[PDB]
Length: 324
Image (cartoon, rainbow, N blue to C red; front, side, top):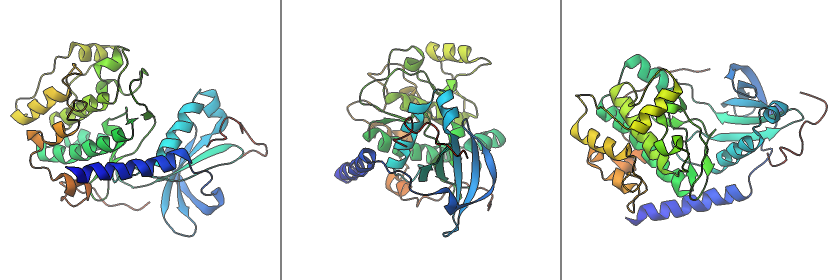
């Protein structure tokens, strides 16, 4: 009943402290040793770095300030960082340090080597229902956490979910996340996951995440998404039709839960009803889920992945990123 209610009061207090005085320049570039490139983002390279004194490894995203200006992403970049430095939940990736210099912004991210659920679902084909359920449980709780903070996630999809070295889920990207009470209108996200009210530009709220959960659950258990096609536009068309076919092996409870998540009518969608998340949590498809044990990372994972161990002399855009 009320153990939940105080956990969330304390979570909000923690979030708001950090959200009202965000932390700045918490480290410096000369503290990290470059190892190699991990990849590329939009504004620059992602580097595997090693903290020179603690020995811990991080994914440091480098962001060219001028390229951020040029791609029209100042506000989104400020906001992403502000959200990341403020949150804290066992299935969310950490922003471990941030800092800036003349040329760049740096986001030193927690680095768990692994491989996305994207690559895993594709090469395994599909997950059994308890396997899907175990991941889904982690997203339910994660959304319950983000939503209590008025944060809409807005980018749920297999590619943003890493399967960690304990086989637990980690949400790895906060690119589209937005803090809003009430409603907002930005068309963003990967087409297969979008709620029809996003596509129709009628404004929408945190309930799109719950539609997107329903999409994810269906994909994990079917091996393919419920709404699909060659072109984004056809995908959008199929969603607005709202004609979901379930595989023959989907249990009754799964189909039941799925009709309530992929539910067009907001007065009926599981998630934002007067009962909120408990409507999902008490749902029959999750009767076997130990919520508390899930949060504590105690449930035995159904699969553990294969182990691994891997600037200008002028100041640029000082005013634009002063809040960074």
